[PDB]
Length: 26
Image (tube, rainbow, N blue to C red; front, side, top):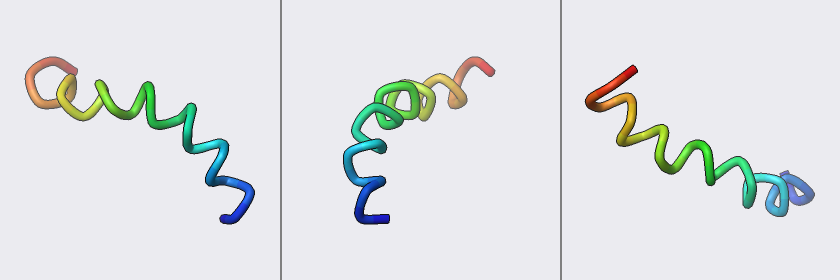
């Protein structure tokens, strides 16, 4: 999505740490 490029910018915040989080914790 062309317009999603700007959206993902914020979605990457919670998804960034979520990656390492799921690793150890839920």
